[PDB]
Amino acid sequence: VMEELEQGLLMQPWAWLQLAENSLLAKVFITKQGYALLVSDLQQVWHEQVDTSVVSQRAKELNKRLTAPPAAFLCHLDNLLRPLLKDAAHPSEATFSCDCVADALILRVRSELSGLPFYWNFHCMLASPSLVSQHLIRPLMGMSLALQCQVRELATLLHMKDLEIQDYQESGATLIRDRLKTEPFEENSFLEQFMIEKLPEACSIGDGKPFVMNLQDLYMAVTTQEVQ
Amino acid sequence: PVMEELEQGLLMQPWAWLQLAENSLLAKVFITKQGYALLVSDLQQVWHEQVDTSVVSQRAKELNKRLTAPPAAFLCHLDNLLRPLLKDAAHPSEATFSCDCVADALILRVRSELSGLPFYWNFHCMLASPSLVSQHLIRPLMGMSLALQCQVRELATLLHMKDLEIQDYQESGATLIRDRLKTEPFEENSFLEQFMIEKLPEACSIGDGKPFVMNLQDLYMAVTTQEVQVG
Protein backbone atom coordinates (compact mmCIF):
# COMPACT_ATOMS: atom_id res chain seq x y z
CA VAL A 1 0.00 0.00 0.00
CA MET A 2 2.31 2.75 1.26
CA GLU A 3 5.35 1.24 -0.47
CA GLU A 4 3.27 0.66 -3.61
CA LEU A 5 2.27 4.32 -3.75
CA GLU A 6 5.82 5.47 -3.04
CA GLN A 7 7.24 3.31 -5.83
CA GLY A 8 4.53 4.40 -8.25
CA LEU A 9 5.28 8.05 -7.53
CA LEU A 10 9.01 7.43 -7.90
CA MET A 11 8.66 5.68 -11.28
CA GLN A 12 6.42 8.40 -12.77
CA PRO A 13 7.50 11.16 -15.19
CA TRP A 14 7.15 14.86 -14.48
CA ALA A 15 4.27 16.73 -16.10
CA TRP A 16 3.60 20.42 -16.69
CA LEU A 17 0.70 22.24 -15.01
CA GLN A 18 -0.58 25.70 -15.96
CA LEU A 19 -2.91 27.45 -13.52
CA ALA A 20 -3.81 31.14 -13.17
CA GLU A 21 -0.67 32.40 -14.96
CA ASN A 22 1.49 30.12 -12.77
CA SER A 23 3.43 27.01 -13.77
CA LEU A 24 4.28 23.85 -11.86
CA LEU A 25 5.92 20.45 -12.32
CA ALA A 26 3.76 17.64 -10.96
CA LYS A 27 4.10 13.89 -10.45
CA VAL A 28 0.93 11.96 -9.58
CA PHE A 29 0.25 8.32 -8.73
CA ILE A 30 -3.33 7.16 -8.10
CA THR A 31 -4.47 3.79 -6.78
CA LYS A 32 -7.54 2.30 -5.14
CA GLN A 33 -5.80 2.58 -1.76
CA GLY A 34 -4.85 6.24 -2.11
CA TYR A 35 -2.82 8.78 -4.04
CA ALA A 36 0.60 10.41 -3.95
CA LEU A 37 1.44 13.85 -5.35
CA LEU A 38 4.74 15.71 -5.70
CA VAL A 39 4.62 19.29 -6.98
CA SER A 40 7.48 21.72 -7.53
CA ASP A 41 8.18 25.19 -8.92
CA LEU A 42 12.00 24.97 -9.23
CA GLN A 43 12.28 26.66 -5.79
CA GLN A 44 10.32 24.45 -3.36
CA VAL A 45 8.97 20.89 -3.47
CA TRP A 46 5.73 19.82 -1.79
CA HIS A 47 4.62 16.22 -1.26
CA GLU A 48 1.24 14.82 -0.21
CA GLN A 49 0.28 11.18 0.36
CA VAL A 50 -3.38 10.45 1.12
CA ASP A 51 -5.08 7.17 2.07
CA THR A 52 -8.72 6.07 2.01
CA SER A 53 -9.83 7.71 5.26
CA VAL A 54 -8.34 11.13 4.51
CA VAL A 55 -9.64 11.20 0.93
CA SER A 56 -13.12 10.17 2.08
CA GLN A 57 -13.19 12.85 4.79
CA ARG A 58 -11.94 15.59 2.46
CA ALA A 59 -14.35 14.60 -0.32
CA LYS A 60 -17.28 14.66 2.09
CA GLU A 61 -16.18 18.05 3.43
CA LEU A 62 -15.73 19.61 -0.02
CA ASN A 63 -18.45 17.91 -2.08
CA LYS A 64 -21.32 18.28 0.38
CA ARG A 65 -23.59 16.38 -1.99
CA LEU A 66 -21.42 13.72 -3.71
CA THR A 67 -21.88 10.35 -1.99
CA ALA A 68 -19.57 7.70 -3.46
CA PRO A 69 -17.04 5.12 -2.25
CA PRO A 70 -13.45 6.36 -1.89
CA ALA A 71 -12.26 3.98 -4.63
CA ALA A 72 -14.67 5.54 -7.13
CA PHE A 73 -13.46 9.00 -6.10
CA LEU A 74 -9.84 7.98 -6.67
CA CYS A 75 -10.68 6.45 -10.05
CA HIS A 76 -12.54 9.58 -11.16
CA LEU A 77 -9.67 11.80 -9.99
CA ASP A 78 -7.22 9.67 -11.98
CA ASN A 79 -9.39 9.77 -15.10
CA LEU A 80 -9.67 13.56 -14.74
CA LEU A 81 -6.00 14.30 -14.07
CA ARG A 82 -3.86 11.72 -15.91
CA PRO A 83 -4.91 12.67 -19.48
CA LEU A 84 -4.25 16.35 -18.77
CA LEU A 85 -0.78 15.68 -17.34
CA LYS A 86 0.18 13.22 -20.09
CA ASP A 87 -0.68 15.57 -22.96
CA ALA A 88 -0.95 19.36 -22.99
CA ALA A 89 -3.45 21.40 -25.03
CA HIS A 90 -6.16 18.95 -24.00
CA PRO A 91 -9.77 20.23 -24.07
CA SER A 92 -9.83 22.70 -21.18
CA GLU A 93 -12.10 21.17 -18.52
CA ALA A 94 -9.98 21.04 -15.33
CA THR A 95 -9.34 24.43 -13.73
CA PHE A 96 -6.54 24.68 -11.17
CA SER A 97 -5.53 27.25 -8.56
CA CYS A 98 -2.73 27.45 -6.00
CA ASP A 99 -2.77 29.17 -2.61
CA CYS A 100 0.64 29.46 -0.94
CA VAL A 101 0.14 29.12 2.81
CA ALA A 102 2.99 30.23 5.06
CA ASP A 103 4.05 26.57 5.35
CA ALA A 104 1.80 24.40 3.16
CA LEU A 105 0.27 24.71 -0.32
CA ILE A 106 -3.41 24.33 -1.22
CA LEU A 107 -4.00 23.15 -4.80
CA ARG A 108 -7.69 23.51 -5.69
CA VAL A 109 -8.95 21.62 -8.74
CA ARG A 110 -12.46 22.18 -10.13
CA SER A 111 -13.71 20.08 -13.04
CA GLU A 112 -16.89 18.91 -14.77
CA LEU A 113 -18.28 15.38 -14.47
CA SER A 114 -21.27 14.79 -16.77
CA GLY A 115 -21.98 18.51 -16.51
CA LEU A 116 -21.80 18.58 -12.70
CA PRO A 117 -19.20 20.39 -10.58
CA PHE A 118 -16.41 18.33 -9.01
CA TYR A 119 -14.07 19.88 -6.44
CA TRP A 120 -10.90 18.55 -4.86
CA ASN A 121 -8.10 20.03 -2.76
CA PHE A 122 -4.51 18.85 -2.33
CA HIS A 123 -2.97 20.00 0.97
CA CYS A 124 0.74 19.57 0.24
CA MET A 125 3.35 20.06 2.96
CA LEU A 126 6.99 20.82 2.25
CA ALA A 127 8.70 17.72 0.90
CA SER A 128 11.09 15.96 3.25
CA PRO A 129 14.81 16.38 2.49
CA SER A 130 15.18 12.68 1.69
CA LEU A 131 12.19 12.51 -0.67
CA VAL A 132 13.10 15.64 -2.63
CA SER A 133 16.71 14.48 -2.93
CA GLN A 134 15.79 10.98 -4.11
CA HIS A 135 13.24 12.36 -6.58
CA LEU A 136 15.24 15.22 -8.13
CA ILE A 137 18.93 15.38 -7.23
CA ARG A 138 20.10 11.79 -7.63
CA PRO A 139 18.04 11.15 -10.81
CA LEU A 140 19.17 14.43 -12.38
CA MET A 141 22.71 13.46 -11.41
CA GLY A 142 22.34 10.15 -13.25
CA MET A 143 20.88 11.83 -16.33
CA SER A 144 23.80 14.26 -16.42
CA LEU A 145 26.33 11.43 -16.22
CA ALA A 146 24.48 9.40 -18.87
CA LEU A 147 24.41 12.39 -21.22
CA GLN A 148 28.14 12.90 -20.64
CA CYS A 149 28.71 9.26 -21.62
CA GLN A 150 26.52 9.77 -24.70
CA VAL A 151 28.59 12.82 -25.69
CA ARG A 152 31.81 10.84 -25.27
CA GLU A 153 30.49 7.99 -27.43
CA LEU A 154 29.36 10.45 -30.11
CA ALA A 155 32.81 12.04 -30.02
CA THR A 156 34.36 8.61 -30.57
CA LEU A 157 32.01 8.06 -33.52
CA LEU A 158 33.03 11.45 -34.95
CA HIS A 159 36.68 10.46 -34.59
CA MET A 160 36.02 7.26 -36.54
CA LYS A 161 34.14 9.15 -39.26
CA ASP A 162 36.88 11.80 -39.51
CA LEU A 163 39.53 9.09 -39.84
CA GLU A 164 37.58 7.45 -42.64
CA ILE A 165 37.07 10.81 -44.39
CA GLN A 166 40.83 11.33 -44.22
CA ASP A 167 41.32 7.86 -45.70
CA TYR A 168 38.97 8.69 -48.58
CA GLN A 169 40.62 12.05 -49.22
CA GLU A 170 44.13 10.56 -49.22
CA SER A 171 43.24 8.25 -52.15
CA GLY A 172 40.03 9.27 -53.89
CA ALA A 173 38.41 11.40 -56.56
CA THR A 174 37.08 14.93 -56.27
CA LEU A 175 33.65 15.68 -54.83
CA ILE A 176 30.63 15.69 -57.13
CA ARG A 177 29.30 18.49 -54.89
CA ASP A 178 31.87 20.74 -53.21
CA ARG A 179 29.29 22.22 -50.81
CA LEU A 180 29.28 19.05 -48.67
CA LYS A 181 32.85 19.47 -47.40
CA THR A 182 33.19 19.28 -43.62
CA GLU A 183 36.06 20.38 -41.40
CA PRO A 184 37.77 17.90 -39.06
CA PHE A 185 36.09 17.61 -35.67
CA GLU A 186 37.92 18.89 -32.58
CA GLU A 187 36.42 18.11 -29.18
CA ASN A 188 38.05 21.10 -27.46
CA SER A 189 37.08 23.57 -30.19
CA PHE A 190 33.51 22.27 -30.33
CA LEU A 191 33.13 22.42 -26.55
CA GLU A 192 34.52 25.96 -26.40
CA GLN A 193 32.30 27.17 -29.24
CA PHE A 194 29.18 25.62 -27.72
CA MET A 195 29.92 27.04 -24.26
CA ILE A 196 30.66 30.53 -25.57
CA GLU A 197 27.74 30.75 -28.02
CA LYS A 198 24.76 28.52 -27.24
CA LEU A 199 25.06 27.72 -23.52
CA PRO A 200 23.03 30.82 -22.49
CA GLU A 201 20.02 29.56 -24.46
CA ALA A 202 20.68 25.82 -24.13
CA CYS A 203 20.83 25.96 -20.32
CA SER A 204 17.91 28.40 -19.96
CA ILE A 205 15.57 26.50 -17.64
CA GLY A 206 12.77 29.05 -17.77
CA ASP A 207 9.65 27.74 -16.05
CA GLY A 208 10.47 24.03 -16.41
CA LYS A 209 8.61 23.36 -19.66
CA PRO A 210 11.76 22.41 -21.64
CA PHE A 211 12.79 19.85 -19.01
CA VAL A 212 9.48 17.98 -19.19
CA MET A 213 9.30 18.39 -22.98
CA ASN A 214 12.84 17.22 -23.82
CA LEU A 215 14.37 14.53 -21.60
CA GLN A 216 11.64 12.84 -19.57
CA ASP A 217 12.45 9.42 -21.05
CA LEU A 218 16.02 9.62 -19.74
CA TYR A 219 14.68 10.61 -16.31
CA MET A 220 12.32 7.63 -16.27
CA ALA A 221 15.06 5.24 -17.37
CA VAL A 222 17.50 6.55 -14.75
CA THR A 223 14.89 6.29 -12.00
CA THR A 224 13.93 2.75 -13.03
CA GLN A 225 17.59 1.71 -13.05
CA GLU A 226 18.08 3.28 -9.61
CA VAL A 227 15.09 1.31 -8.31
CA GLN A 228 16.87 -1.95 -9.17
CA PRO B 1 27.33 43.51 1.58
CA VAL B 2 29.33 40.81 3.37
CA MET B 3 26.42 38.37 3.39
CA GLU B 4 25.65 38.94 -0.30
CA GLU B 5 29.33 38.51 -1.19
CA LEU B 6 29.46 35.27 0.80
CA GLU B 7 26.34 33.95 -0.92
CA GLN B 8 27.66 34.83 -4.38
CA GLY B 9 31.05 33.26 -3.66
CA LEU B 10 29.42 30.09 -2.37
CA LEU B 11 27.19 29.92 -5.44
CA MET B 12 30.16 30.35 -7.79
CA GLN B 13 32.23 27.82 -5.82
CA PRO B 14 32.20 24.26 -7.23
CA TRP B 15 31.72 20.96 -5.43
CA ALA B 16 34.53 18.87 -3.96
CA TRP B 17 34.89 15.38 -2.50
CA LEU B 18 35.84 14.92 1.17
CA GLN B 19 36.61 11.40 2.43
CA LEU B 20 36.64 11.76 6.21
CA ALA B 21 35.91 8.58 8.21
CA GLU B 22 34.61 5.38 6.58
CA ASN B 23 32.48 7.79 4.53
CA SER B 24 32.64 10.75 2.18
CA LEU B 25 30.68 13.93 1.49
CA LEU B 26 30.31 16.59 -1.18
CA ALA B 27 31.46 19.94 0.22
CA LYS B 28 31.45 23.49 -1.11
CA VAL B 29 33.03 26.21 1.04
CA PHE B 30 33.78 29.90 0.46
CA ILE B 31 35.78 31.70 3.17
CA THR B 32 36.57 35.42 3.24
CA LYS B 33 38.11 37.63 5.91
CA GLN B 34 34.62 38.66 7.09
CA GLY B 35 33.24 35.13 7.52
CA TYR B 36 32.51 31.99 5.56
CA ALA B 37 29.78 29.86 4.01
CA LEU B 38 29.67 26.07 3.79
CA LEU B 39 27.33 23.64 2.03
CA VAL B 40 27.74 19.90 2.56
CA SER B 41 25.74 16.94 1.31
CA ASP B 42 25.73 13.15 1.04
CA LEU B 43 23.28 12.90 -1.90
CA GLN B 44 20.48 12.38 0.66
CA GLN B 45 20.50 15.50 2.87
CA VAL B 46 21.98 18.98 2.47
CA TRP B 47 23.36 21.07 5.34
CA HIS B 48 24.29 24.76 5.16
CA GLU B 49 26.18 27.05 7.53
CA GLN B 50 26.85 30.77 7.08
CA VAL B 51 29.11 32.19 9.79
CA ASP B 52 30.38 35.68 10.67
CA THR B 53 33.45 36.88 12.58
CA SER B 54 31.95 37.25 16.07
CA VAL B 55 30.73 33.66 16.29
CA VAL B 56 34.01 32.60 14.65
CA SER B 57 35.96 34.06 17.56
CA GLN B 58 33.48 32.71 20.11
CA ARG B 59 33.59 29.13 18.79
CA ALA B 60 37.36 29.25 18.25
CA LYS B 61 37.88 30.19 21.89
CA GLU B 62 35.35 27.59 23.05
CA LEU B 63 37.18 24.87 21.11
CA ASN B 64 40.91 25.64 21.21
CA LYS B 65 40.90 26.87 24.84
CA ARG B 66 44.56 27.94 24.49
CA LEU B 67 44.77 30.02 21.27
CA THR B 68 44.23 33.79 21.03
CA ALA B 69 44.09 35.05 17.43
CA PRO B 70 41.89 37.53 15.55
CA PRO B 71 38.96 36.02 13.62
CA ALA B 72 40.43 37.14 10.29
CA ALA B 73 43.64 35.18 10.90
CA PHE B 74 41.63 32.16 12.06
CA LEU B 75 39.56 32.21 8.87
CA CYS B 76 42.67 32.67 6.73
CA HIS B 77 44.32 29.65 8.37
CA LEU B 78 41.12 27.61 7.99
CA ASP B 79 41.04 28.45 4.28
CA ASN B 80 44.72 27.59 3.90
CA LEU B 81 44.03 24.22 5.53
CA LEU B 82 40.84 23.41 3.61
CA ARG B 83 41.26 24.76 0.06
CA PRO B 84 44.35 22.69 -0.91
CA LEU B 85 42.63 19.53 0.33
CA LEU B 86 39.46 20.32 -1.63
CA LYS B 87 41.27 21.22 -4.86
CA ASP B 88 43.10 17.89 -5.17
CA ALA B 89 42.90 14.48 -3.51
CA ALA B 90 45.68 12.67 -1.64
CA HIS B 91 46.98 15.99 -0.31
CA PRO B 92 49.23 15.50 2.75
CA SER B 93 47.60 18.37 4.65
CA GLU B 94 47.58 16.54 8.01
CA ALA B 95 43.85 17.30 8.27
CA THR B 96 41.49 14.90 10.05
CA PHE B 97 37.74 15.15 9.42
CA SER B 98 34.97 13.64 11.55
CA CYS B 99 31.18 13.80 11.33
CA ASP B 100 28.45 13.55 13.96
CA CYS B 101 24.82 13.50 12.79
CA VAL B 102 23.44 14.47 16.19
CA ALA B 103 19.68 15.16 16.04
CA ASP B 104 18.96 17.06 12.79
CA ALA B 105 22.10 19.22 12.91
CA LEU B 106 25.47 17.98 11.66
CA ILE B 107 28.76 18.60 13.46
CA LEU B 108 31.80 18.46 11.16
CA ARG B 109 34.99 18.43 13.24
CA VAL B 110 38.30 19.39 11.62
CA ARG B 111 41.64 18.77 13.35
CA SER B 112 45.06 19.86 12.11
CA GLU B 113 48.67 20.37 13.20
CA LEU B 114 49.29 24.08 12.56
CA SER B 115 53.10 24.20 12.35
CA GLY B 116 53.23 21.19 14.65
CA LEU B 117 50.62 22.38 17.15
CA PRO B 118 46.94 21.45 17.59
CA PHE B 119 44.21 23.32 15.73
CA TYR B 120 40.52 22.44 16.09
CA TRP B 121 37.36 23.70 14.42
CA ASN B 122 33.71 22.64 14.23
CA PHE B 123 31.05 23.37 11.62
CA HIS B 124 27.56 23.21 13.15
CA CYS B 125 25.64 22.90 9.90
CA MET B 126 21.84 22.97 10.04
CA LEU B 127 19.47 21.49 7.48
CA ALA B 128 19.75 23.45 4.24
CA SER B 129 16.85 25.76 3.49
CA PRO B 130 14.57 24.53 0.68
CA SER B 131 15.40 27.54 -1.50
CA LEU B 132 19.17 27.29 -0.98
CA VAL B 133 19.34 23.58 -1.80
CA SER B 134 17.12 24.15 -4.82
CA GLN B 135 19.19 27.00 -6.27
CA HIS B 136 22.45 25.18 -5.54
CA LEU B 137 21.66 21.65 -6.79
CA ILE B 138 18.34 21.27 -8.62
CA ARG B 139 18.29 24.19 -11.06
CA PRO B 140 22.01 23.97 -11.97
CA LEU B 141 21.74 20.21 -12.48
CA MET B 142 18.76 20.48 -14.82
CA GLY B 143 20.42 23.31 -16.71
CA MET B 144 23.44 21.03 -17.11
CA SER B 145 21.16 18.27 -18.38
CA LEU B 146 19.58 20.60 -20.95
CA ALA B 147 23.00 21.80 -22.09
CA LEU B 148 24.19 18.21 -22.50
CA GLN B 149 21.03 17.37 -24.46
CA CYS B 150 21.74 20.29 -26.79
CA GLN B 151 25.33 19.07 -27.15
CA VAL B 152 24.04 15.60 -28.06
CA ARG B 153 21.67 17.08 -30.65
CA GLU B 154 24.55 19.07 -32.14
CA LEU B 155 26.68 15.93 -32.29
CA ALA B 156 23.84 14.03 -33.96
CA THR B 157 23.36 16.68 -36.65
CA LEU B 158 27.12 16.78 -37.25
CA LEU B 159 27.03 12.99 -37.63
CA HIS B 160 24.22 13.42 -40.16
CA MET B 161 26.28 15.94 -42.16
CA LYS B 162 29.28 13.60 -42.10
CA ASP B 163 27.07 10.73 -43.28
CA LEU B 164 25.73 12.87 -46.12
CA GLU B 165 29.30 13.67 -47.15
CA ILE B 166 30.11 9.96 -46.88
CA GLN B 167 27.22 8.98 -49.14
CA ASP B 168 28.38 11.62 -51.61
CA TYR B 169 31.91 10.19 -51.58
CA GLN B 170 30.56 6.67 -52.13
CA GLU B 171 28.36 7.85 -55.01
CA SER B 172 31.45 9.53 -56.50
CA GLY B 173 32.77 6.05 -57.39
CA ALA B 174 35.67 5.98 -54.91
CA THR B 175 36.85 2.77 -53.24
CA LEU B 176 38.63 2.42 -49.90
CA ILE B 177 42.09 0.88 -49.85
CA ARG B 178 41.28 -0.80 -46.51
CA ASP B 179 37.83 -1.95 -45.41
CA ARG B 180 38.92 -2.57 -41.81
CA LEU B 181 38.25 1.12 -41.11
CA LYS B 182 34.80 1.14 -42.75
CA THR B 183 32.06 2.62 -40.57
CA GLU B 184 28.31 2.04 -40.90
CA PRO B 185 25.58 4.69 -41.22
CA PHE B 186 24.45 6.29 -37.96
CA GLU B 187 20.82 6.35 -36.81
CA GLU B 188 19.74 8.41 -33.80
CA ASN B 189 17.00 6.00 -32.73
CA SER B 190 19.14 2.88 -33.04
CA PHE B 191 22.08 4.45 -31.22
CA LEU B 192 19.84 5.75 -28.43
CA GLU B 193 18.19 2.36 -27.92
CA GLN B 194 21.54 0.54 -27.97
CA PHE B 195 23.02 2.96 -25.43
CA MET B 196 19.99 2.71 -23.15
CA ILE B 197 20.06 -1.09 -23.26
CA GLU B 198 23.82 -1.51 -22.82
CA LYS B 199 25.66 1.37 -21.15
CA LEU B 200 22.99 3.27 -19.19
CA PRO B 201 23.25 1.03 -16.07
CA GLU B 202 26.98 1.78 -15.75
CA ALA B 203 26.92 5.44 -16.80
CA CYS B 204 23.93 6.56 -14.71
CA SER B 205 25.52 5.16 -11.54
CA ILE B 206 26.60 7.90 -9.14
CA GLY B 207 27.92 5.87 -6.21
CA ASP B 208 29.19 8.28 -3.56
CA GLY B 209 29.14 11.22 -6.00
CA LYS B 210 32.77 11.09 -7.14
CA PRO B 211 32.07 10.96 -10.91
CA PHE B 212 30.15 14.24 -10.73
CA VAL B 213 33.01 16.21 -9.19
CA MET B 214 35.42 14.43 -11.55
CA ASN B 215 33.59 15.04 -14.84
CA LEU B 216 30.74 17.55 -14.36
CA GLN B 217 32.28 20.62 -12.72
CA ASP B 218 33.16 22.98 -15.58
CA LEU B 219 29.65 22.70 -17.01
CA TYR B 220 28.29 23.25 -13.50
CA MET B 221 30.46 26.36 -13.21
CA ALA B 222 29.18 27.75 -16.51
CA VAL B 223 25.54 26.98 -15.72
CA THR B 224 25.77 28.59 -12.28
CA THR B 225 27.50 31.66 -13.73
CA GLN B 226 24.78 32.01 -16.37
CA GLU B 227 22.04 31.60 -13.75
CA VAL B 228 23.52 34.26 -11.47
CA GLN B 229 24.04 36.58 -14.45
CA VAL B 230 20.38 36.20 -15.44
CA GLY B 231 19.24 37.09 -11.92
Image (cartoon, coloured by chain):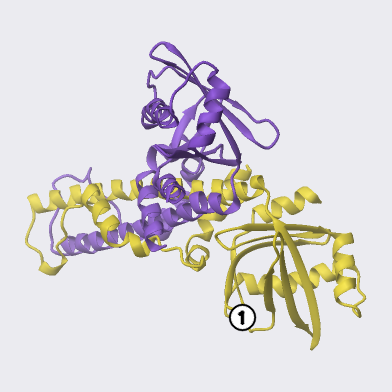
Chain colours: A yellow, B purple
User: Residue A133 placed where, x, y %?
Assistant: 60, 47
Q: Is residue B36 visible?
A: yes
Q: What's the residue at 74%, 81% (across, down)?
A: A111
Mark 1, secondary structure of its residue? loop
Q: Name the residue nearer the viewer: B53 or B123.
A: B53
**Front-most of residues B155 and A61:** A61
Expressed as whole percent of the image width and height from the top left, the position of residue A105 reads 70, 64
For disc 1, the neighbor class at 10 Å (few under 14, some 14 to 19, many from 20) is few
Q: Position of residue B58 (x, y in %)?
A: 55, 29
Question: Where, by quadrant of the figure, is residue A202 drawn?
Answer: bottom left
Residue A31 x/y as whole percent:
78, 61
Left or right: A223 as drawn, with respect to B135: right
Q: Quadrant of residue A176?
A: bottom left
| Residue lying at the far top of the rendered structure | B116
Q: Nearer the viewer, residue B16 or A134?
A: B16
Q: Is residue B68 above or below residue A93?
A: above
Q: Nearer the viewer, residue B172 or A190?
A: A190
Image quarter of residue A125? bottom right
Circle 1 residue: A90
Residue A154, compared with residue A76, is above or below; it is: above
Chain on which label 1 sits: A
Amino acid type, callout 1: His
Relative horizontal placement of residue A69, taking residue A161 as reference (left or right) = right
- Asked whether, in this view, residue A208 is left or right of residue A100, the answer is left
Quarter of the figure that contains the C terminus of chain A? top right
* Number of numbered labels in the structure image: 1
| Residue B187 in sight here | no
